[PDB]
Length: 145
Length: 145
Length: 48
Image (cartoon, each protein chain N blue to C red):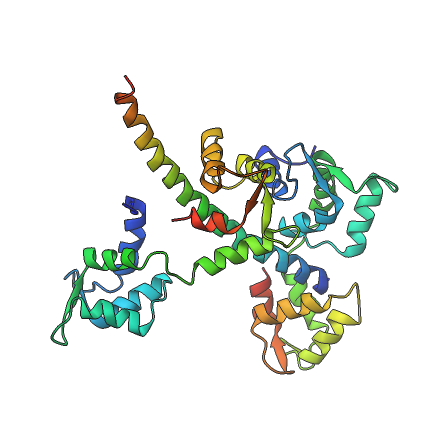
């Protein structure tokens, strides 16, 4: 289960712009429109396959739970990973894509959501059991989802 | 002492992206970076002054309380955007709210401390500039705020 | 006066972007860690 309630809340906030009737099931052309409004970018062909799954007649609709299911079916194949890669390419002090395990634990001890000992221990464990004091930037994108 | 506990916390959080070891000390190389990030708009010569005020031989390293003392030296200044709208009026031909791209290029690279080639490139890309024309300073200061 | 404010704004803008991305990433990792912790504590019902 990728989901938690506060994710579903923002997806419903976006979907409320389209459910102007309270009907809860959206015609084919809206699917890609909602996804790109949220920021996820499937191609017209990738959308055409997801339309083939539901609309055999030229008039089908997609219920809110199948819309969330289609979003999940297209979760990690996204152009929005490339912005997170960019944030690390800005932050890197050497410009070579590798950061200190000391720097990582220090930043996480002090900044943002502010991670505890067990959360930082788990974050280091999530990268590599073979890690020798240094961490590749892309693995931070890989633990995101 | 010149900052509240909330202000100290905000500045400590930001400083902990540039201090990388958490012992309470920054390199002079990122001292400009952290101050420019924390709302300040210091000149190159003012960074040079603030370092040589602490030590004129030194070690290229500055304690967190000494960094907060540099922030204290700035925070007296009543800085706000209306004087910047007024700063662009000095380069308007008509009073229309507009600086020419040629005059702006002269302003950025002949007068004053001077922006580098990449600072100009980076700004042009962010600004959505197209052709050697003119740019509205009311809209631009709204973006700069 | 103009130059130093643009220099400030460039760094401050990419800093604002970076912080938004980092905090989103940390919130997603904190969900993942909690959904691992939840699996861990259950098997103390069996390590008995």
